[PDB]
Image (cartoon, grey):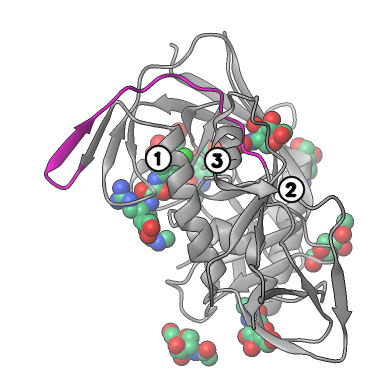
Amino acid sequence: KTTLFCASDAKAYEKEVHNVWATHACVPTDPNPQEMVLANVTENFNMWKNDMVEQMHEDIISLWDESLKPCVKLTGGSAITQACPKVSFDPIPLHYCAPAGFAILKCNNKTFNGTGPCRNVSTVQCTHGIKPVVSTQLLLNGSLAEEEIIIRSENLTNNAKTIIVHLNESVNIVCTRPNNIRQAHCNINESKWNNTLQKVGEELAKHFPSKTIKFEPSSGGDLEITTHSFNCRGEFFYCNTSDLFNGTYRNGTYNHTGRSSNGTITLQCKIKQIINMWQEVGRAIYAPPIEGEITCNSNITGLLLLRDDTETFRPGGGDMRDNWRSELYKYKVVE
Ligand SMILES: CNCc1ccc2c(c1)[C@@H](CC[C@H](O)CO)[C@H](CNC(=N)N)[C@H]2NC(=O)C(=O)Nc1ccc(Cl)c(F)c1
Ligand SMILES: *[C@@H]1O[C@H](CO)[C@@H](O)[C@H](O)[C@H]1NC(C)=O
Ligand SMILES: *[C@@H]1O[C@H](CO)[C@@H](O)[C@H](O)[C@H]1NC(C)=O
Ligand SMILES: *[C@@H]1O[C@H](CO)[C@@H](O)[C@H](O)[C@H]1NC(C)=O
Ligand SMILES: *[C@@H]1O[C@H](CO)[C@@H](O)[C@H](O)[C@H]1NC(C)=O
Ligand SMILES: *[C@@H]1O[C@H](CO)[C@@H](O)[C@H](O)[C@H]1NC(C)=O
Ligand SMILES: *[C@@H]1O[C@H](CO)[C@@H](O)[C@H](O)[C@H]1NC(C)=O
Ligand SMILES: *[C@@H]1O[C@H](CO)[C@@H](O)[C@H](O)[C@H]1NC(C)=O
């Protein structure tokens, strides 16, 4: 309804590009903030129609555009050329804050699905701290649901609308390019994944009860969405998930079809130089990888899925606003 401002706990003395950007663009965070609880008020939210998501998307585009400058950027006809130094890159949490005369309403219902009326509302001045993690297929390093796993979607009947699965227990994913320079791998504990997908299958079953629930790899698209793509320490990883989204939840029970080995699923990854931009329709070319080992140790806290008797779910993503929504769903700007 208005322009918000960001608060961060950044350094003016870290090189780290999120810190640098935040110190120019954000004010410091309040040491202990004010919350007001209003259980009686009961208010409507719609996470799919949230101006905060667009404000954040604008900001993260700015951050990346100042911070991960490509050597060449191809948009439409033009090519744009510039210094592309290797940088230290590790997302930091950002708080979105209502300016004077406005507030931010938090929905406090642990099982709120992001849409409709919420009973226990709070009013606050800033959101919690959200790390702006850009990625596809798997949401990384977010905040978990307190209770159950929530299933969010603008329209679950519309199979074109992205489904956000909000997890209540994180699943570790470790991705490394060890010390072929492009080639890397990720390890996930197959038991832990096995479980998580048991219970996602349960929740999806509640919303589609006659059908049998299948997980299958991403059918088609650019590499950025047919793989789990993400930025680790400045390098763009593209990780094959066909052993991850590969299972059936039949009748109260999940089978995992992808292989594992010693009880780990290992995804093969490539580090790539030509990137299809998430900010706009265009290509970006970056310099070859830094040497050393590049390793990111991340929590999977959510999934982005797309639905095609049986219902079949594929990993999705590509619109980073869905990543922001997964964090901003319980917030609304008012007054
Ligand atoms: C779900 N709706 C379908 C769908 C699907 C894929 C994509 C979109 C929409 C566009 C969304 C644009 C948005 O509206 C911007 O405002 C976006 C266009 N971009 C092009 N080059 N064609 C395109 N997504 C990407 O390319 C992308 O995610 N790449 C990428 C790179 C680096 C990293 Cl690390 C990364 F994790 C991801
Ligand atoms: C979310 O909850 C609302 C009611 O609050 C309901 O109308 C809607 O269908 C639900 N959506 C999902 C995806 O569960
Ligand atoms: C998480 O939610 C699932 C599905 O909603 C539920 O079955 C499970 O008991 C919950 N687990 C934890 C650890 O909270
Ligand atoms: C969402 O689903 C379909 C679109 O396929 C349509 O009936 C309408 O847009 C929505 N329906 C419901 C029940 O919300
Ligand atoms: C989950 O993974 C563990 C470890 O590999 C395995 O022993 C168990 O049977 C699996 N459960 C399934 C596939 O339902
Ligand atoms: C992932 O790996 C499988 C088998 O290794 C292959 O069939 C599939 O095309 C790969 N997907 C991508 C996007 O590389
Ligand atoms: C599941 O994995 C196996 C081997 O890991 C592969 O042969 C199969 O094609 C995968 N399933 C799908 C639907 O791709
Ligand atoms: C997730 O957080 C950990 C700890 O801050 C970090 O090491 C890791 O690189 C993060 N993952 C991504 C993809 O940013």
**To which residue does mark 2 refer?**
194
Crowd rating for badge 3 (residues with CA inside 10 Å; few <14, some 14–19, many 20+):
few
Residue 116 image-quadrant placement: bottom right
* Comes first in the chain, label 1 or label 3: 3
Q: Which residues are magenta?
A: 75-92
Tell me, yes or no, if residue 175 can be seen here.
yes
Q: Position of residue 11 (x, y in %)?
A: 68, 32
The outermost residue toward the left is: 77
Of badges 3 and 2, nearer the viewer stands 3
Residue that appears at 70% across and 55% down: 197
Magenta stretch, overall SS: loop
Task: Give the image quadrant in which the ligand numbered 8 is located.
Answer: top right
Q: Is residue 74 left or right of residue 211?
A: left
Mark sitting on residue 215: none
On-image quarter of the C terminus: bottom right
Circle 1 SS class: helix
Work out whether 160 lies above or below 263.
below
Q: CA distance from mark 1 to mark 2?
A: 38 Å
**Amino acid at pointer 3:** His
**To which residue does mark 1 refer?**
65
Residue 319 image-quadrant placement: bottom left
Q: Position of residue 196 (x, y in %)?
A: 75, 53
Q: Position of residue 149 (x, y in %)?
A: 76, 64
Residue that appears at 72% across and 68% down: 150
Residue that appears at 30% across and 35% down: 284
Of badges 1 and 3, nearer the viewer stands 3
Front one among 150 and 243 = 150
Q: Position of residue 253 (x, y in %)?
A: 75, 61
* Comes first in the chain, label 1 or label 2: 1
Work out whether 139 lies above or below 68.
below
